[PDB]
Image 1 (cartoon, rainbow, N blue to C red):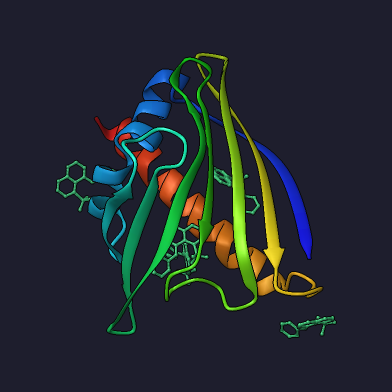
Image 2 (cartoon, rainbow, N blue to C red):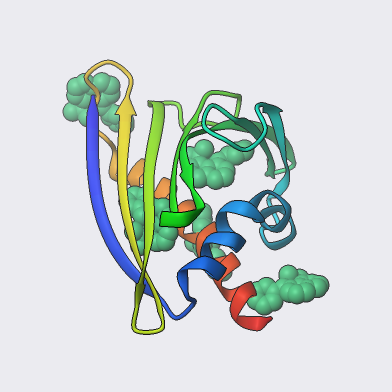
Length: 152
Ligand SMILES: O=S(=O)(O)c1cccc2cccc(Nc3ccccc3)c12
Ligand SMILES: O=S(=O)(O)c1cccc2cccc(Nc3ccccc3)c12
Ligand SMILES: O=S(=O)(O)c1cccc2cccc(Nc3ccccc3)c12
Ligand SMILES: O=S(=O)(O)c1cccc2cccc(Nc3ccccc3)c12
Ligand SMILES: O=S(=O)(O)c1cccc2cccc(Nc3ccccc3)c12
């Protein structure tokens, strides 16, 4: 089953700085800022579309990973589209979740435009708990980096 959500939020950080921290320096900063995430390793490609990253994390003493695949990336338009799937750490009811993110200038800061598509196994509805967990983690990473950028 396919479940789509669209959201907008704002940041006081201007788009080039926010894009650089979250997308270009994200693989270095995320493990430093999020206790559970141990590493983000490129397993295929060189940072362009098709690049696959292995994200390893620890929870309740156990180690697992998921795969992050770049669908599109363009620095000039602050565009970053990526898919989370597979590995040993992914939500059981999900085949994949695809993200389309875009920043634009707003009021000295950034407007953030997101489109999120959950692909559930078979014809399963998206449980509230799975929506909530993917959203909290997505927000957590983005907002940990944003706070870091504000501190510097
Ligand atoms: O929980 S997931 O829904 O995959 C998830 C969804 C959205 C963003 C995520 C970012 C990093 C790690 C995740 N999970 C993860 C879990 C265990 C080990 C490694 C990564 C993320
Ligand atoms: O949502 S339901 O209407 O039961 C449902 C309806 C139709 C197909 C479903 C397939 C898998 C899991 C479900 N439920 C489920 C229940 C608890 C937790 C996670 C998924 C499905
Ligand atoms: O939560 S939001 O404020 O849009 C948000 C804020 C900042 C960064 C985000 C990155 C990915 C998805 C989001 N939203 C999202 C929406 C539904 C499900 C999962 C994530 C992000
Ligand atoms: O902790 S929980 O709400 O369970 C939580 C569980 C899973 C993912 C989370 C992502 C961001 C923030 C949380 N809360 C949080 C609460 C206090 C300080 C920092 C983060 C998340
Ligand atoms: O991760 S902390 O452990 O604080 C940390 C530890 C050691 C050095 C740090 C340098 C800059 C920012 C941090 N964190 C940070 C995160 C969000 C907002 C402001 C600062 C640093």
